[PDB]
Amino acid sequence: KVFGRCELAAAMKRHGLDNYRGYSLGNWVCAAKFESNFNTQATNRNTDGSTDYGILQINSRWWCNDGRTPGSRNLCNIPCSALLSSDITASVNCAKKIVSDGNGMNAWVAWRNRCKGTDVQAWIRGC
Ligand SMILES: [Cl-]
């Protein structure tokens, strides 16, 4: 599915992302916009043989297991296929582990380049 902006904000808030590990909700909404364009089924292959999966483009080298990525660590202990559900639970649970690993939201390239430093609260304004 393709979430609306406020629709995703409300779902992410219900799943505990607002202010999680220091990151207000607008950060997470902006990240999803620029990672997946709010599409729960987005996938993108990378040069290292990994693929990024779902609404938050979670990577198959470090975080989820897709069975075809060399050097897999599966630190979220989740099959990547689960991260293509229209229900965001598995992606949020893995994102919480990623953002707790020591480098904040820097794991999300699109967030680093297109959200960080902007007024991210605009992403939840009006919701
Ligand atoms: Cl604005």
Image (spheres, rainbow, N blue to C red):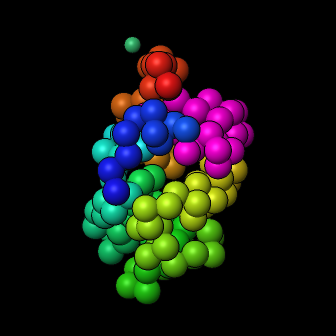
Query: In screen coordinates, is 51 left or right of 61?
Result: left
Query: In screen coordinates, is 94 left or right of 46?
Result: right
| Residue at 33% in and 62% down | 41
For residue 59, which quarter of the picture? Answer: bottom left
The one of 37 and 13 positioned closer to us in this rendering: 13
Asked if one can make out residue 98 in the rendered structure from this viewpoint, the answer is no
Asked if one can make out residue 26 in the rendered structure from this viewpoint, the answer is yes
Q: Number of numbered discs present?
A: 0
- Which quarter of the rendered picture does the N terminus lie within? bottom left
Residue 71 % position (x, y): 48, 79
| Residue at 42% in and 29% down | 115
| Residue at 69% in and 50% down | 100
Query: In screen coordinates, is 96 left or right of 63?
Result: right
Identify whether 35 is placed above or below 119. Answer: below
Residue 99 % position (x, y): 63, 48
| Residue at 51% in and 49% down | 107
Identify whether 77 is placed above or below 96. Answer: below
Q: Which residues are magenta?
A: 11-30
Identify whether 61 is placed above or below 89. Answer: below
Residue 10 % position (x, y): 55, 38
Name the residue at the bottom extreme: 67
Residue 21 % position (x, y): 71, 40
Q: Quadrant of ligand 1?
A: top left
The stretch drawn in magenta includes residue 14: yes
The one of 103 and 51 positioned closer to us in this rendering: 51
The stretch drawn in magenta includes residue 78: no
